[PDB]
Amino acid sequence: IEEGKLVIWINGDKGYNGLAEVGKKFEKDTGIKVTVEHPDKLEEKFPQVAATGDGPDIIFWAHDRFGGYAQSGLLAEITPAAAFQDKLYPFTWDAVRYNGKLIAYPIAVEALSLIYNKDLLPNPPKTWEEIPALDKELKAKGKSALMFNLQEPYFTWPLIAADGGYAFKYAAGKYDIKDVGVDNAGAKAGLTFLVDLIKNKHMNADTDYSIAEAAFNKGETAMTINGPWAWSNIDTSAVNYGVTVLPTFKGQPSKPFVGVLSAGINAASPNKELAKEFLENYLLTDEGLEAVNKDKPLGAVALKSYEEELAKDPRIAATMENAQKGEIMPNIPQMSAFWYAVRTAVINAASGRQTVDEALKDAQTAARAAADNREIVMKYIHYKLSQRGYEWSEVVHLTLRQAVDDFSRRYRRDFAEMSSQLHLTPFTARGRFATVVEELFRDGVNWGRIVAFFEFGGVMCVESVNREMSPLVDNIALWMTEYLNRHLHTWIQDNGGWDAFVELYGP
Ligand SMILES: O=C(c1cc(-c2cc3c(cc2C(=O)N2Cc4ccccc4C[C@H]2CN2CCOCC2)OCO3)n2c1CCCC2)N(c1ccccc1)c1ccc(O)cc1
């Protein structure tokens, strides 16, 4: 990373040209050049370059991914003065607090809202229950009432959780990844109404984001559920649209997941002092957010001064109101298990493979099982790193401990050749893991090849620390946990579970 310059990454759906004007003004006053870039899939590319102590000085993304960045050690801790913290809404600072430390600057507050075509529907519906009768009237005119992305649970969650569902319980400065709140009567009521809409032919089950967006922007549907990142495309379609509070369900408000667009500073950047000055003194100002906002809308903003003026726009007041009625999105990589489990529950309940009550009950069991598989992966990687001097029933953990130790000892000559020939880069790390794991289980699954599965991820975690790519260990731990949840768990339970592993290997 070049010292004396500021390289900034931000997604293309944001006002990156407005941010470039703020950097241009910063360059005139400091002599420090600010280069703003908008790479494709920067949320995947940032952990790769930052693992080798490289990449942008500043990254813009939602707060939920910054938890994984902070735990990896990719983001530097920010320490704003108390006079500057009072300028941002305190809940936005909460979304960027991890292990009791602030790891990002909050910028904008993103949340889903109800977007309606005023020409097709001058008065939008205030309740979900009156939507079916509305679709019937619009169907006679060749239009549907509501289309939105049904494939991602992020968009269906406002309705599902409106009557009491929650993703993870939060306590003691951490999320409880075993206390999942999808198995409740409220969520089953929300998922039932969603399935009823599909089975009554009010929505198509395979509608995704692009299908819904194109349908609303062309006037084919009266309403949609989307965030401020889509307002720019509706503007160019000339659809006279309004943005309002999400409909209520059983008299209870829809609670969407709240996302805090946040600016993190690379922990390897040599210009952290400059990045803090640019973020606090230039961007996080009324004039700085306005420059970005006028390029592309941010929705609600964390800066109280500029949010008070933006709230005059009904679209932004609705976004803030829908955010206040929602909940902050958990900022942990375990949400991938939550999303994966909930998505299957919705897919299966809509298709009819299982009941709504069974789908959410199984999704809660699957989420709790993922936490248990993570426990096995983490406890092994901690032991392997501790052997090398590095720092990061319980019988199964000590059984696997003896199994991997024996495997490494019996094939130590082979592990020495592998480690010396291994060329590990964050760009090619995911490919090497996927290729090897495929070869391990290509001809079937047994306990011996599962022990080898753990030991391979272990040596990749140790070799990552050696090549000064320590944050890559959290990515490998995530891949091992994913493969254990989605592939090996079918074989493990069918062959006696982990209790059969301690029966063959244990004492
Ligand atoms: O390519 C591999 C690899 C390792 C094993 C493997 C798995 C086992 C096992 C055995 C072996 C095995 O075949 N080896 C063990 C081993 C261990 C460490 C490093 C290299 C090797 C290669 C050979 C060597 N032996 C020598 C004695 O005669 C039999 C073969 O017993 C029970 O489970 N298998 C493969 C590929 C698919 C077949 C099984 N890695 C790999 C990965 C990257 C680069 C090179 C090899 C790999 C995958 C997972 C691991 O935990 C370790 C290695």
Image (tube, rainbow, N blue to C red):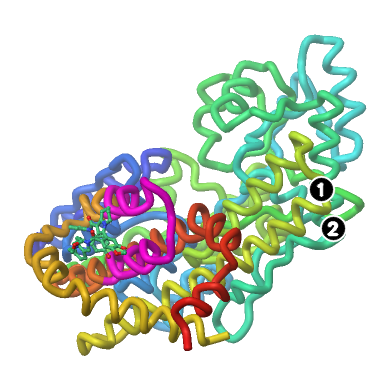
Left or right relative to 501: residue 188? right
- The N terminus lies in which quarter of the figure? bottom left
In what quadrant does ligand 1 lie? Answer: bottom left
Question: What is the span of residues highlighted in magenta in the rendered image?
Answer: 433-458
Q: Secondary structure at mark 2?
A: helix
Residue displayed at 53% across by 56% down: 491
Q: Quadrant of residue 140?
A: top right
Left or right relative to 162: residue 48? left
Q: Secondary structure at mark 1?
A: helix
Q: Nearer the viewer, residue 156 or 491?
A: 491
Q: Nearer the viewer, residue 55 or 392?
A: 392
Tell me: is circle 1 under 8 Å from ligand 1.
no
Name which residue type carries label 2.
Gly
- Mark 1 is surrounded, within 10 Å at the Cα level, by few (under 14), some (14 to 19) or many (20 or more) other residues, namely many
Q: CA distance from mark 1 to mark 2?
A: 11 Å
Whether 381 is among the magenta residues is no
Q: Earlier in the sequence, mark 1 or mark 2?
A: 2
Between disc 1 and disc 2, the foreground one is 1
Q: Which mark is residue 186?
A: 2
Name which residue type carries label 1.
Val
Q: Is residue 207 above or below residue 362?
A: above
- Mark 2 is surrounded, within 10 Å at the Cα level, by few (under 14), some (14 to 19) or many (20 or more) other residues, namely many
Residue displayed at 86% across by 51% down: 189
Residue displayed at 91% across by 51% down: 250
Residue displayed at 73% across by 59% down: 325
Residue linked to disc 1: 356
Residue 189 seen in this snapshot:
yes
Q: Decide whether the magenta segment is chiefly helix, strand or loop.
A: helix
Q: Is residue 145 above or below residue 96?
A: above
Tell me: is circle 2 under 8 Å from ligand 1.
no
The percent position of residue 498, horizontal first and vertical second, equals: 54, 72
The percent position of residue 461, horizontal first and vertical second, equals: 26, 70
